[PDB]
Amino acid sequence: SALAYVMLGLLLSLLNRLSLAAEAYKKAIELDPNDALAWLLLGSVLEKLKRLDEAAEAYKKAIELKPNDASAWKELGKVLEKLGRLDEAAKAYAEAIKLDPSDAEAAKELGKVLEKLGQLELAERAYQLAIELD
Amino acid sequence: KMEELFKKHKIVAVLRANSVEEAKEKALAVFRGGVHLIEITFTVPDADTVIKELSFLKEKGAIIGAGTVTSLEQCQKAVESGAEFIVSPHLDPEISKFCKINGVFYMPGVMTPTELVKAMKLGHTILKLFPGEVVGPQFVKAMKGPFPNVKFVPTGGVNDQNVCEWFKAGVLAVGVGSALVKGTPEQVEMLAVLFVAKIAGCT
Image (cartoon, rainbow over all chains, first blue to last red; front, side, top):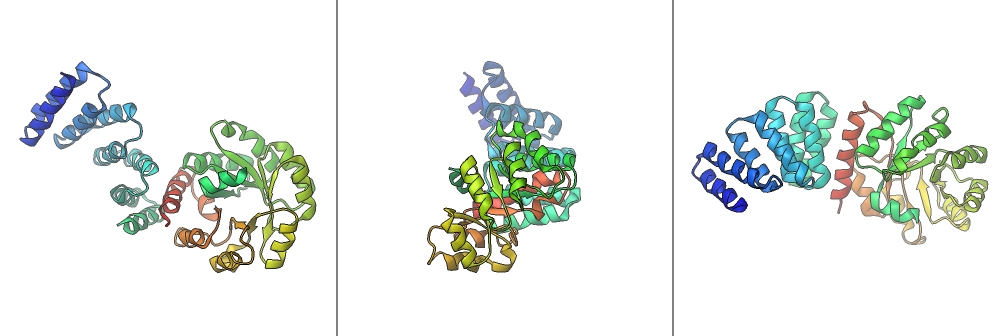
């Protein structure tokens, strides 16, 4: 039943009933607290539900399970950038590039965070990395 | 050997600071940024104490060594401090004998073909190309013919715009110093993860 509720949340996410999908992922979490897919999907659903403070907590719980997901770190960078922790998001985008230096999106989004944070030289070096990848 | 460790991490942090506490901060940021080869130059006052105070990073998987060694008596304090490799900007034959007997890896400074031959006769096949901003990657690609065994780790003129030119020429690693040293102890960690990414992306 742990997997079935995850498939239920995926189906509900296809019908834009996101709040109903979040309840499905949470039920699979109660059944198995170590299901990293349930945590990662819950973070991406709450991100679109704009529960950004709760969304980052599920993304951190997903990274705590599988600490080598460039998708989870990059998605945590989107939430923390929209939430307001620009320096904590740049540290999250950094861990995403440590795992995959070919992620053209993570390098482009890190240059945007650094450009708003101050260091144009650190941002420019990140912009050129993303441009060379694609 | 140390060569296989140079071939893996492919980057050496030529750390130059002013105080002892300033050096320990930048070494922590560089290691957190993914760079495991840290070259602590002896121009830093009391560099033999910085190397022995960073001994805990050798458990975390860091290779701390002493760089810019002018005299052999300076290499005495370098080996006794706990450095795992000795680096000099010039070729000093008496330092090579001391590092061979004590069992420490030594990378001399070479700029000419004759300085390379004299360093090869001492048994060295891994030389430091100082200053790389004068010889250029064309030098490394030129010595690939007559000396197919020498492996260069340049120090000068190695920036992010041409870091792939050095590697595609035939270098073993690169020693970035000015780019990694400049910045706050949090900008230094970010500068490392950006430099490690470009090296991994080179063809």
